[PDB]
Amino acid sequence: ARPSSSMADFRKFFAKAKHIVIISGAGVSAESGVPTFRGAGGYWRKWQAQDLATPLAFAHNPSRVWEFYHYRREVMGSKEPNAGHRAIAECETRLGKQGRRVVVITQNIDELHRKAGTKNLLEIHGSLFKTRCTSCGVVAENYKSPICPALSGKGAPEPGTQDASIPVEKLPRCEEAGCGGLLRPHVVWFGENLDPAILEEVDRELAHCDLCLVVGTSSVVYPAAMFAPQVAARGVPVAEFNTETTPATNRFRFHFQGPCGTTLPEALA
Amino acid sequence: XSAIKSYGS
Ligand code: NA
Ligand SMILES: [Zn+2]
């Protein structure tokens, strides 16, 4: 069931849409130079993101998981939103002044949509720049470089790099009085439940959508991979913007190849 | 539709 590659046709749908949902994934961050540690060429040491972003990995080797997230936090300091992020933010602003809604549902944890100025933003998997205490549950913003002294200079990505093996007491710890708990990234890991309040907001946006754009996602991680297919199955137009086809491509009305930073400025003008 | 994050097989 081959989707259309006609931008002119897509633009006629775009012109009429009053409730656009944009779902974004790791490819949009990759176009800003962010290492995603997914796909055929994405590895930190000898692992991919889905090997380390798990409760079991964190239970068995919290130092290694923290090294991985520390590396990613520090690299992000030098990364900026790309033309795709900017086109999405500019579109939201322009349509909002016309009484038309754009909402971004991002799988990404990098805060690049936020940095680009997107306002209607659902970060469905949390953030690299938030911590949660495993003892008291408090969630906090954390941009500190480095997040703790023991991690300074650690997290190097080359294969064969030795574990830092930081004692748990010297990994990031809660600073609330009397707690002292071990912090973790406030990131939804593989095997964990997404936040119910966020899923309810997603459900409402999808149910009312009249055009859905699926941008830079491989459509292999659930639940997010089912969002756009659910809309399409009700007849709602979906346009996939991706450098490759995915398992979901043939469910959608349009497929546009190339970097999202090249195609979205045209599509959303 | 599951609220559990899963790298689909
Ligand atoms: Na993705
Ligand atoms: Zn605490």
Image (spheres, coloured by chain):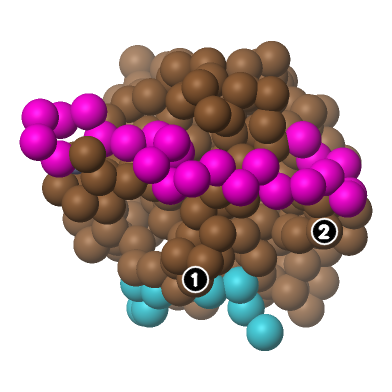
Q: Which mark is residue A46?
A: 2
Label 2 lies in what chain?
A: A
Chain appearing in cyan on the rendered image: B
Residue A167 in the magenta stretch? The answer is yes
Quarter of the image with the C terminus of chain A in it: top right
Amino acid at the residue labelled 2:
Lys
Figure label count: 2
Span of residues in magenta? A156-179
Q: Earlier in the sequence, mark 2 or mark 1?
A: 2
A166 over A117 or under it: above or below: below
Q: Residue at x 87, y 42 (%)?
A: A158
Amino acid at the residue labelled 1:
Leu
Both marks 2 and 1 on one chain: yes
Q: Quadrant of residue A186?
A: top left
Q: Residue at x 23, y 62 (%)?
A: A196
Q: Residue at x 55, y 59 (%)?
A: A61
Q: Quadrant of residue A199?
A: bottom left
Chain appearing in brown on the rendered image: A
Q: Quadrant of residue A69?
A: top right
Distance between the alpha carbons at the discs numbered 2 and 1: 17 Å
Depth check, front residue: A150 or A131: A150
- Answer few, some or many: residues within 10 Å of disc 1's Cα (few below 14, many 20 plus, some between 14 and 19): some
Q: Which mark is residue A112?
A: none
> What x and y, as percent, mark residue A148?
46, 25
Q: Which residue is mark 1?
A: A56
Judged from the image, the secondary structure of the residue bearing numbered disc 2 is loop
> What x and y, as percent, mark residue A85?
61, 26
